[PDB]
Amino acid sequence: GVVAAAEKTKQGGVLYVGSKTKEGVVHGVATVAEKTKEQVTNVGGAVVTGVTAVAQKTVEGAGSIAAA
Amino acid sequence: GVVAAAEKTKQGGVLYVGSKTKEGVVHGVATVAEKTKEQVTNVGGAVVTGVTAVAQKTVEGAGSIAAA
Amino acid sequence: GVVAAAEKTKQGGVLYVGSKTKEGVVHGVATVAEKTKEQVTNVGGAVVTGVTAVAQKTVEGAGSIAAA
Amino acid sequence: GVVAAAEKTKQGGVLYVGSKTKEGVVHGVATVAEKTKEQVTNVGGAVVTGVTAVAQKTVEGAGSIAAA
Amino acid sequence: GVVAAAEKTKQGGVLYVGSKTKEGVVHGVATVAEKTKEQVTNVGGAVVTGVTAVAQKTVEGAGSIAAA
Amino acid sequence: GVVAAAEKTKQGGVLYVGSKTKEGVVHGVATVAEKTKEQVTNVGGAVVTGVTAVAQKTVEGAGSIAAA
């Protein structure tokens, strides 16, 4: 077996982004493996997919992951 | 199998995003495996999929995953 | 056998997003595996799928997952 | 056998989104497997599908999943 | 045998979305498997399917159920 | 077996980005491995995918990861 965990606590801005380009297909995070036993896809913190996508002050939480 | 847990506690702005492009198909996070036995797809925190998608101040909880 | 759990506790805005593109089919998070014993699809935190979809201040709760 | 549980406790806004595209079929989270024994499809937290769908402040609850 | 349970306790807003596209069929979360013995579909937290359907402040409850 | 965890505590802006060039497909982070058994994909902190995508003051939380 395995264990993992996280928590957040607390005890105590402009940005200009315009998209312009003629094409984009986007894959955020991705993998392949043929003839494979233990294909495990894991994602944490913040990740987002968009042909434009923005991360102001984005992760104030916390986290961790494990596998196999 | 596997065991895990998480929590939040608490004890104590502009953004400009304009889409413009002629096409985009999008896949957020994805994987494939043929002739394959133990396919496990895991996602946590915040992840979102859109041709535009935005992550302002987004993850303020906490998290973890583990598998297989 | 298997166990998992989560909770939230507590003890103590602008964004401009305009979509514009001529096409997009979108699949949020997805997988395939032919000839497969243990196909397990798990999703937690926040995930949503839309040709535009947005994550303002989104995950203030908390969570975890495990499998197989 | 198998076990899972979750709870919430508590002890203590703008967004502009306009859809515009000429087409989109969308499938939110999906999987397929031919000749396959134990297909288990699980979804938690928040997930929704719509050609636009938005996740303002969305998950304040908590949750978890396991299978097999 | 098998176990799962949950409930909620407590002890202590704008969004603009207009749909516009010429077509989209949508199926929210779905899976298929031919020649399959233990075909199980499970859904928790918040889920709905609609050509637009929206997840403002959506899961204030908590949950799980778990399988096989 | 395996163990890992993280937390955050606390006890105590202009930028100009206009996208313009004629095309870009972008993949955030990705890998492939044929005939390979233990495919593990893990991501944390903040990373985001967009042909323009921006990281003002982005990770003030913390985390770490391990596998296999």
Image (cartoon, coloured by chain):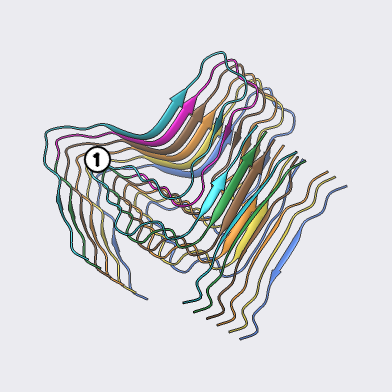
Chain colours: A green, B brown, C orange, D yellow, E blue, F cyan
Position of D67 relative to B8 (above/below): above
Quadrant occupied by the C terminus of chain B: top right
Quadrant occupied by the N terminus of chain B: top right
Provide residue F45's location: percent of width, then percent of height.
46, 50
Residue A33 is left or right of residue A4, and the answer is left
Q: Chain of mark 1?
A: F
Main secondary structure type of the part rendered in magenta: loop
Residue B44 visible within the image: no
Q: Is residue B57 magenta?
A: no
Which span is picked out in magenta? A21-49
Q: On the image, which quarter does residue F26 sit in?
A: top left
Q: Measuring 65% from the left and 43% from the top, which residue is drawn there?
A: B66
Residue C41 is left or right of residue E40, and the answer is left
Residue F50 is left or right of residue D60, and the answer is left
Q: Which residue is mark 1?
A: F51
Provide residue B67's location: percent of width, then percent of height.
67, 39
User: Between E61 and E37, which is closer to the camera in this rendering?
Assistant: E61
Residue type (three-letter) at the residue carrying disc 1: Val
Provide residue D3's location: percent of width, then percent of height.
79, 52
Q: Is residue A22 magenta?
A: yes
Residue F58 visible within the image: yes
Residue B49 is left or right of residue C67, and the answer is left
**Label 1 neighbour load within 10 Å: few <14, some 14-19, many 20+:** many
Asked which secondary structure carries label 1, the reply is loop
Q: Residue furthest right?
A: E1
User: Between F50 and C21, which is closer to the camera in this rendering?
Assistant: F50
Position of C9 relative to F32 (above/below): below
Disc count in the image?
1
